[PDB]
Amino acid sequence: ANVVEGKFHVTGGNVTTAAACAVDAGSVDQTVQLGQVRTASLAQEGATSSAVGFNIQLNDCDTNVASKAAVAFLGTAIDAGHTNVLALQSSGSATNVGVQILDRTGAALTLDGATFSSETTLNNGTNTIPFQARYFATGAATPGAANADATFKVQYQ
């Protein structure tokens, strides 16, 4: 079967050395398995794969410093018409498919480093901000490796 298969590698941390929370060491460098998806499921612009979850955990939060956190992601957009779809790493790579990062509301986030996820209202101590990643077809996907990379920054308000 013709499939696209790959992983989403994400690294990141706080914008500022002096932040309301610490980013958990398990969250600052993660690799998310996107799975193997048949190109017949990605044969048309706007087709998407089943999303895979990944979390960003924040520790030791002090809500006297900030009551909310949000995350912005940076990565190469697959093309000017899909600024919320990551380009793939070129390594036998798939084409006409990229990777989207969704926040807890299901919105695919723009990948320009300035577009923040929906805000998470913090409790003191540990808080998790959930995300999902998935494949997004920009056309008739072709089989091959489909890895993507992005970086994130946590901002507080």
Image (spheres, grey):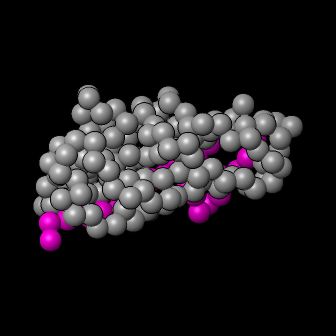
> Residue 55's image quarter?
bottom right
In the rendered view of the protein, which quadrant contains the C terminus? top right
Q: What residue do we see at 28% from left, 42% from top?
A: 46
- From this viewpoint, is residue 151 visible? no
Question: Horizontal and vertical percent for residue 86?
Answer: 33, 43
Give the x, y percent position of residue 71: 57, 40
Question: Quick check: is 33 in the magenta stretch?
Answer: no
User: What is the residue that sits farthest to the bottom in this orientation?
Assistant: 1
What residue do we see at 76% from left, 44% from top? Answer: 122
Q: Residue furthest right?
A: 64
Question: In the displayed structure, would residue 88 be above or below residue 73?
Answer: below
41 or 134: nearer the eye? 41
Q: Is residue 133 left or right of residue 58?
A: left
Quadrant of the drawing holding the N terminus: bottom left
For this rendering, which residue is in front, 155 or 17?
155
Is 23 part of what is drawn in magenta? yes
Vertical relation: 17 (above or below) 149: above
Residue placed at 56% from the left, 37% from the top? 117
In the displayed structure, 6 sits above or below 88; it is below
- Left or right of 121 in this view: 32: left
Of residues 95 and 139, the one drawn nearer to the viewer in this rendering: 139
- In the rendering, at what x and y percent does residue 138 appear? 22, 41
Question: At x 22% / y 53%, what residue is drawn?
Answer: 42
Image-based side of 146 in relation to 14, left or right: left
The residues colored magenta run 1-28
Asked whether 143 or 10 is in front, the reply is 143
Whether residue 21 is visible, yes or no, is yes
Label total for image: 0
Which image quarter: residue 78? Answer: top left
Where is residue 142 drawn, in percent x and y? 13, 55
